[PDB]
Length: 32
Image (cartoon, rainbow, N blue to C red):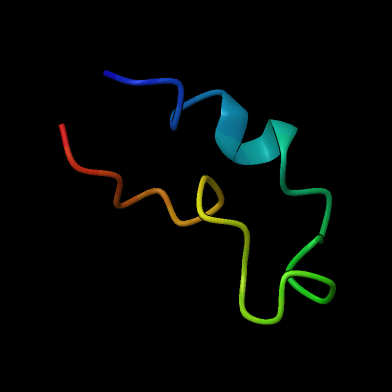
């Protein structure tokens, strides 16, 4: 599993506002 597991919460402190939708790593649907 990529960093998308841990970095999900790491780069997404409710950053969904500034990132428009949500941070790409906040979207824990990251491909393998």
